[PDB]
Length: 117
Image: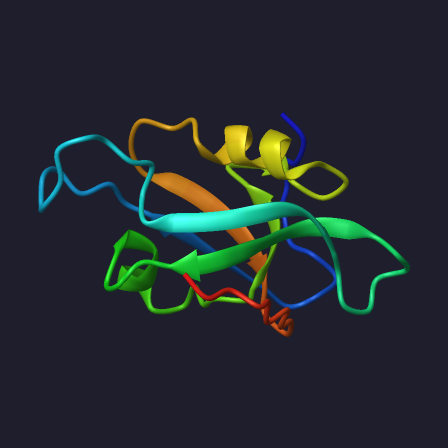
């Protein structure tokens, strides 16, 4: 419980959902091919931390959508905000959903981190 009548933001964001795929090519159990790192300063914000999509798997659930892109600032995930949190905390928030999930990222925004692997 938080929003009711219309839940839009003042800034341009892209609210896309991620559906879970039943079997494909794995034998462990992951929380969608979506990775986001928290406790990272935002480019522009007044010395504030947030969460951004570290990277995206090769043709995963996140990439499946097409919208979601690497180096994108995630405003909120599954409703739960990641801003003003920590990598771990965030992760936990993310790594905790058996099935489709909802992500709230910003449109006009690019972090671009030194992510090799």
